Image (cartoon, rainbow, N blue to C red; front, side):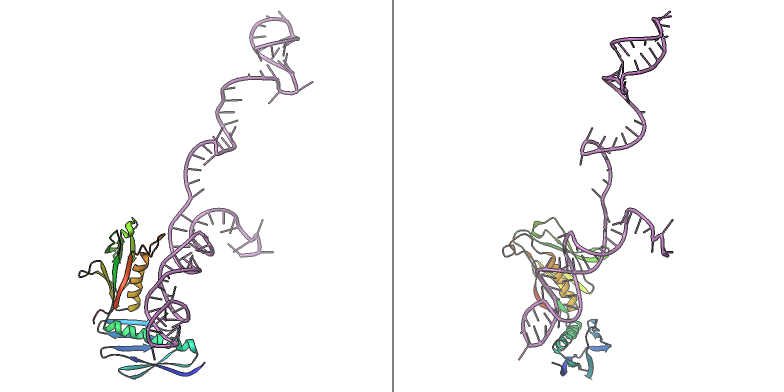
Length: 189
RNA sequence: CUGUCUGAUCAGGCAACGCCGCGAAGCUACCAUCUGCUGGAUUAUGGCUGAACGCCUCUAAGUCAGAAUCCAUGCUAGAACG
């Protein structure tokens, strides 16, 4: 409808410094550094003070304005991943065949190896994204821990694990086997 | 091997390739043998992050995987005015 101005406020906490130039966003915190490129969006940024940043769209229509909240949420995930971390938990679900999951290394590169899924002889390997750590949890039986600074990478790599274990040619309501994301939270609470 | 002709023998001619067995060479037969490649991008579909719409949502920005599909690799010709 061509709204004259739309604003969003980024709350940037005590231990972070969000550096922005030409829609390239670099968020430094106690757990490291995260970068995001936003050259595909027409937005502008204002430093209100050290603890707040204003994000603005001028003369935007409905969809251009819809992108504004998305921009703010993405940068906020950057901040909360550089200060609090991100941790996704996966549980192994099976009826008869135990799912054997190991973190192996080939070509000097880390992989997640899933064996005996529904008794299949095929072995499944999922490449581990950069900055994402996998860890077989010890407190809980049959649980995988996916952690990292980037919410996007951690969630995508957990989804890669969940999608590789789809059941074919069966009633999935009955054959409920798989590896599913059970908890989505933060490393430090 | 038959009939006939060269007097006989030897050696030959002819039968509008005379007839029969074998027959190399060459050609040839799923009637024989050999050989038929591996990268990227997608469709349907299933997802991630995520607004619009304080919630939600695979979608709007962004993004992942994925078909005998598509484009290459490979193969054939080589523009007779490249």
